[PDB]
Amino acid sequence: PGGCSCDHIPGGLKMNCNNRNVSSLADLKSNVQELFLRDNKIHSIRKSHFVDYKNLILLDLGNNNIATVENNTFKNLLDLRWLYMDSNYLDTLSREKFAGLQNLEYLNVEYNAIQLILPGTFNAMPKLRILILNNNLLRSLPVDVFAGVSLSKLSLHNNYFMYLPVAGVLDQLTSIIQIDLHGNPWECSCTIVPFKQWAERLGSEVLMSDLKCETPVNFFRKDFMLLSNDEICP
Image (cartoon, rainbow, N blue to C red; front, side):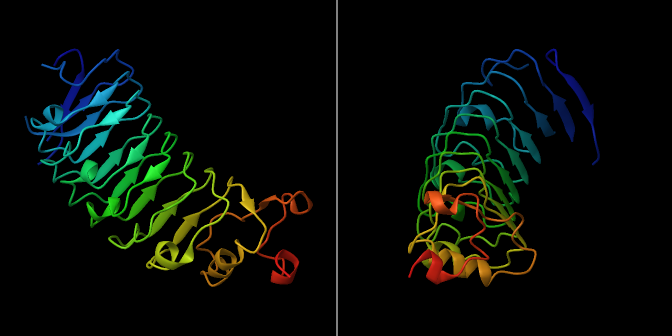
């Protein structure tokens, strides 16, 4: 209904519309808890699309062509805990776009074109525990971006970071148990030293992968966790 597989789980229907040629969201025929919309061709999502769905606990929008997301799109969605939005084309993230998600725990937005995260974007989802932001076009993070949430795992690898500000952005990262930061063009200079120290003051296994330098040329693929500060900045 219509043309998509359906089944119900205690105590909630599940909808499987994957690899089906789907242009928009308003083209369907509630008590729907799980909605699978992966590998389709959805250009954008609007408030109107999810007014009907208020019982969703899992919303998978993967490998779509989502370019824009209207403000207050997920406002009526309070049962939603897991939101997959990967391999889409999201330019920026704002607080207004994620309003309404109070019980969201896991947010995945990897392989997008995210170039900027607006201040207090993640204040919208207070119960957020896992944040996936890897493989994007990020080059900087705003102050107090992680102030609103207590994250256990964060994935920022494969972006375009050359440095990271500790005060206001990384110092507010508590309850951290896993963090990923690789494939990033780190520069070994006087600017990377504060980030180096924070990474050294981290837990033994909280850092998932080793961080290696990109510039200058003389420190190519060299773990700066081992290097001394005088080598980097005399």
